[PDB]
Image: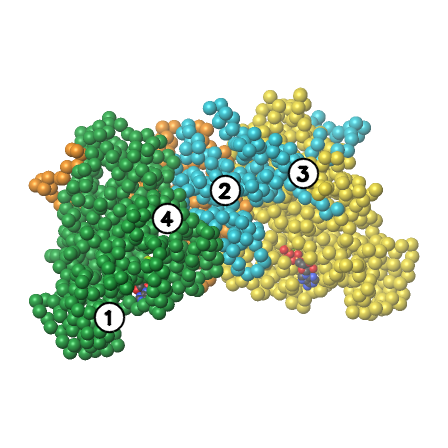
Chain colours: A yellow, B green, C cyan, D orange
Amino acid sequence: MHHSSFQPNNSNFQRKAGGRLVLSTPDVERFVILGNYGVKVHQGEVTIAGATLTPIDDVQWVHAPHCHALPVLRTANDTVIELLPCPTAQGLRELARLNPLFGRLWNETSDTFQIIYTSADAPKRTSLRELASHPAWNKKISELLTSTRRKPSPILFICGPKSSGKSTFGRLLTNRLMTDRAGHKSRSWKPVMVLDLDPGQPEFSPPGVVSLTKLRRPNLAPPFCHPGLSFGNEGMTTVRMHAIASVTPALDPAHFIACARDLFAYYRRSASQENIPLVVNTPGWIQGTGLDLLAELIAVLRPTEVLYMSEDGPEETVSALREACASSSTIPFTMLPSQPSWTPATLRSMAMQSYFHLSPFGPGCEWNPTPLTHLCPWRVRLAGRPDERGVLGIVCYDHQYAPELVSDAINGMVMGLVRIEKKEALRGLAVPGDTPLLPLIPNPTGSPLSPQYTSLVGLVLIRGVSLTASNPELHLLTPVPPSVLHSFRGDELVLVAGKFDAPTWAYVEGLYWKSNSKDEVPWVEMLH
Amino acid sequence: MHHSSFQPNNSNFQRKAGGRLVLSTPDVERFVILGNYGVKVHQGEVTIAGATLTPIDDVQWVHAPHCHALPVLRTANDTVIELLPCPTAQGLRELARLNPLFGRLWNETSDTFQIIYTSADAPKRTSLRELASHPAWNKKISELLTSTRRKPSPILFICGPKSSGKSTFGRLLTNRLMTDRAGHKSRSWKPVMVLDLDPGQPEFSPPGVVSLTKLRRPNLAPPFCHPGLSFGNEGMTTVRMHAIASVTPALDPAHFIACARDLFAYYRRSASQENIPLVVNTPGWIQGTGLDLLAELIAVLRPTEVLYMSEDGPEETVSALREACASSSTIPFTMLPSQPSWTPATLRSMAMQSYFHLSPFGPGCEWNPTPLTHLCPWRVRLAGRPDERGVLGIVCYDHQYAPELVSDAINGMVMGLVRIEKKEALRGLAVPGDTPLLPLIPNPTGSPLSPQYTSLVGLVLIRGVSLTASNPELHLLTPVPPSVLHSFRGDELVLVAGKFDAPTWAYVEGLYWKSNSKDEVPWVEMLH
Amino acid sequence: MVQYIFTPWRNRAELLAVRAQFYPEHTSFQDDEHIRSEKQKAVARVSMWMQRGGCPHMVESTALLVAAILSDEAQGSGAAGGYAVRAAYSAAFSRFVTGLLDSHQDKQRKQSMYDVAKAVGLPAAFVELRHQATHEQLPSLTRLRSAARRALEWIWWYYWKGLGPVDQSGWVLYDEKEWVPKPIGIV
Amino acid sequence: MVQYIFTPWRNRAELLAVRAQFYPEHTSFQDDEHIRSEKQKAVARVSMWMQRGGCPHMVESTALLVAAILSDEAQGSGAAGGYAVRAAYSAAFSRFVTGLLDSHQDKQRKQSMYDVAKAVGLPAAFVELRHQATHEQLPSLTRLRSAARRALEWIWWYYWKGLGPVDQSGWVLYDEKEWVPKPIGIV
Ligand SMILES: Nc1ncnc2c1ncn2[C@@H]1O[C@H](COP(=O)(O)OP(=O)(O)OP(O)(O)=S)[C@@H](O)[C@H]1O
Ligand SMILES: Nc1ncnc2c1ncn2[C@@H]1O[C@H](COP(=O)(O)OP(=O)(O)OP(O)(O)=S)[C@@H](O)[C@H]1O
Ligand SMILES: [Mg+2]
Ligand SMILES: [Mg+2]
């Protein structure tokens, strides 16, 4: 039953029961599956996008967005699978009413997931790629894996020119290293840490933030399907983040490298006990300042192996990289192939928008489909005392401002709550005093707050400042749960406002919701 | 006797007597003649570089520099000529001891002029061009000439892209219009006025000066063989000059056009009585501001005929020119051919250097071969009263200066004595008062002195300023005869210091003379 | 509903106000003082907009030119020595010309700067000055003064005139009972 | 006797003196005052040399950079508003880089800016900044400050250190009897 060819292949008896699909396949059979679905193998072995699943494994929720390369499921001999429907996905689905971009990104049918056959099961006016592993890539991964198993905790530095497959390859490495279970009479799933140093288009983080993440379960989902993680079992937790308020680090190399050091430090500490490999992916530069940064990064981190995903790259960058790589006593540098729409800009924007709608708390993380406008903001005070006021002040990076401008300038943009650990941070800045005007913390220098002394507690969106008559206050909305927010005394909490690329989606969102479900909106000009 | 071929042709009996050459030629015979020589035809008709000479004509001194196109002498039937030696040329010759550039520019023999034959009479390590008139050029000239004779005083506006033959053609026009003597039973030589609006590489003027000249005799000599003319029969006199202190008018279009108006005005006045044509040659631009200037010039002057020496020019400039030309009711615009080393820079420099050595009185003008250093400067006072002081002050164009800088800045460069006619010139400037510092006339605006109220009295080279203890004074040297200098009361005399391109040749000149004939020279650095 | 164009100003009143401040002449010791004051504030404001993102090139160029002119005319030990001012002008000018030409260009290989310049209606003088300013010996103060002022007026007739007429108790979750859904920014 | 190279300064003492004024640090409220004063004079002097003609590109660039830096740090109602200073820096920088690269180039058709830059020994950062500064949105004040200072020091190690150690009675024709032939300039 269910016969077709060229993209999938025949299955056998597909018994639909209670909303789930029990399918038996007595031969090597590969099939694509667009949508949201949980896998729970009963007998046999299945390979899904890099992770091998067997009977003794918990259910794995897989999100397969029609945008990227849809994961392929290949089953190795006579096996029986049960495909469950995903619940939380419904909440994410409803987000299409607040921005049409999320509309054309899933199965255009009725249920949550629809199997795909020869060519006509595809949605209208849209192509449909497919994840395919080159023989080289796979073989290389095998080599690294076998070496790793007979060694300690390796560090893999992945880099290469833009749109080459750095991210995809990283995904494969992470999933396979984690789930492999070779000859040990399987094991359990060995944890894996990921260091994302890509402000441009991050992973496990909102855009404009660098971070270290700890993974327990396989990572089978794009970046915009899990941006924020429960700060502090639990699947994916976030160790530490830093706010590099740009979308191109070429605005302050010093800070960037500093951040890299601090994060790697923490990694060193935790890794030391329980052996856990670290996969780090870089932004992706080749010419100019970027190349220099890559060199310095290699020097500081001292990775076990460097993978350059180009094989036909420019001679200058390859040479430079080889020199730097060779310098740190010895470092294996190997090149691998690549392969040649949604631009990075829109993808980035989607990530950001998804983050703010994350609900403040097998599943991963629910989504709250109610527009940002309708929500109730947090009312923070501004004229108190330096210990009972709320926000200690407002710092600015790479650009100053006069007093009058600040109120209008800050309002509307995205900022970051930054918690001061040790008092050695604000040493040198003329910290405001209790005393109506915004407590702007003058910073003539321009440089950002030291990473070793301060941390990011999640981005914040401002929706209104009213500092008149006798009660200076700010109305801001964040995804951060109330629990953490209350537990900080207010004295140790500064607000950092930089670039971040203005959340244009936010303003319009209210209007879209009102129109689709069925007035002097600032900054948005309607063409009448 | 004297047989050869390909460049000249055989003569006949050449009788040398007393230093002159009497040569008879009973057939159309053409011969080149490099050097300095005076022609005085006894019987027949000879055509030399555009001017037709016959028995009833005074001796014509011809300078034929080996640099440009050597004039060819063609004789029409059985004629007898007497070639005289030039005297004053010896003085010019000696200038080679003060700058090697003037060394390789004449006949490398013994006498003043040496006839040239087939290929081997040429000097060593140097080519030897020849003036050749294209059939088109000649025919066009004939047409203009016949039209002119049956009309009043035409105005010929010659222009075209760089290195095309504008100057050469102009030379031909001037010489032929002047000397022609068609069917009138000859006549006398009809005067001709020339308006030089080319600051870059002028004619009958030093570089950086625009001027109107009146010619009686033919102009058979390059620009660096008569730069200055006896201010105020006499061959060549100068009516009026203006100091546009640059080598590219694209620094102040307003002043340039203003100057054009003033000069043309005077021309109008004098022309009105005694009918005399005017030949004007422009700098030579095609793109940018220059083209616009050319357009405006055509509008203001309203020339009878415009000659564009390109025939393959860019479509944009030709079109633009045609539009402007058409606009002034009707203006015949015709195109003519062209033809494709010493760069303009060096030629310009030679002109300038020649000017200062001019003796104070096809023959024309003697040259004084004594170096500028050895001469005795003019001692002008600076602290007097505004009527018994000498120089009224120092103005600056396109660039100001602070007080302290001025003394060092001015000294060494080339400036211009400017005589104030009507007091309406310095109206608006804070004229200094009698009272030690240089009487700098502040000019915040930047613009130059109005042309309608002031005139140039010849360039001036400064060789030393000593304003200490109690006697502020300047030591300057000029070619201007003492007669004119004394007759100006001092009150009506301002000094203008602009660009002019620093007289680098001046400093070195002393050293060259001393070495060739056989110490902390400022600005010149000797490579030791 | 693609009719959504994002701007960095709050509304049309803010945009018009800035325009007024820049050109008091057309919009209309103590008088000069006030004018200078307003111009300074206007420049500052525009700078903020630039940071915010998505700001028309013309507004930027206008700001630059006014900034230079304003700096040039300043007595009180702030006349910048002379060479500075000349640089400020050259920078603003070069940026302005480069912007205009680059924008209105075709997607062919190598069409010439002059051609594009003529097609858009930009005086060849400006283009020439641009080329000279960048490579061939930084222009004199007087030329820059003239060029700057002309540039400003030209800009006015090109862009700005088409914009209208010419006359722990520190964090309290907001009460879920007295709240009303308002858009982002308004209070 | 082709050993004649023309310079716009009077002699080596004038050239060295200017160098001293520009970089008091290596050559060596009231102290700061004096330093600022000297720097201003130095800039003015260099400007004059430029007018005179035939002046090394490096000296020009140095003057520009110092001019901008000097303007930036000026209290007393002369801080130029903010946008001006950022322009002054961008101009000086762009000129400096363009000059160096254009000079040390080959007479082939279209060799790349980066190649030449590397060959001469100029940090790729500067070239990148140049490209960005001219076209892609004028740089921030902080970046410009850093880049300018680095540029200055680099210039010092490239050019200036190789110049030495480191420790009607108004017109009277002059009397043809008491005159002695002296060169042009000296009195
Ligand atoms: N072998 C492959 N099979 C399927 N898709 C592939 C393959 N190789 C590349 N792609 C596609 O290449 C695109 C880029 O993937 P990435 O791994 O993000 O490359 P990248 O270089 O990391 O992109 P940036 O610039 O870093 S965000 C994806 O949309 C993949 O679908
Ligand atoms: N028919 C010709 N016969 C001889 N020499 C010619 C002829 N045509 C052009 N030349 C040469 O062309 C050169 C340039 O002559 P010009 O008449 O000065 O041209 P031009 O365009 O006026 O140059 P500029 O740029 O204006 S100084 C001279 O050296 C002439 O020798
Ligand atoms: Mg990627
Ligand atoms: Mg000519």
Q: Is mark 4 within 8 Å of ligand 2?
A: no
Please name the residue that numbered disc 4 is placed on: B249
Please name the residue that numbered disc 3 is placed on: A523
| Crowd band around label 4 with a 10 angstrom C-alpha radius: few (<14), some (14–19), many (20+) | many
The nearer-to-camera label among 1 and 3 is 1
Q: Residue B74 carries which label?
A: 1
Q: Where is residue D176 in the image (x, y as percent from the top left)?
A: 9, 42
Kind of residue at disc 1: Arg
Kind of residue at disc 4: Pro
Could you tell me which chain the residue with mark 2 belongs to?
C
Could you tell me which chain the residue with mark 4 belongs to?
B
In front here: B295 or C111? B295
Callout 2 secondary element: helix
Residue drawn 12% across the image and 67% down it: B20
- As measured in the structure, the alpha-carbon distance from the residue carrying label 2 to the one carrying label 4 is 21 Å
Question: Which of the four quarters of the rendered structure image does ligand 3 lie in?
Answer: bottom right
Quick check: C29 above or below B83?
A: above
Residues marked 1 and 2 touching at CB (< 8 Å):
no
Please name the residue that numbered disc 2 is placed on: C151
The nearer-to-camera label among 3 and 2 is 2
Residues indicated by labels 3 and 2 sit on the same polypeptide chain = no
Q: Where is residue C106 in the image (x, y as percent from the top left)?
A: 58, 56
Residue drawn 18% across the image and 65% down it: B55
Quadrant where the image shows the C terminus of chain D: top left
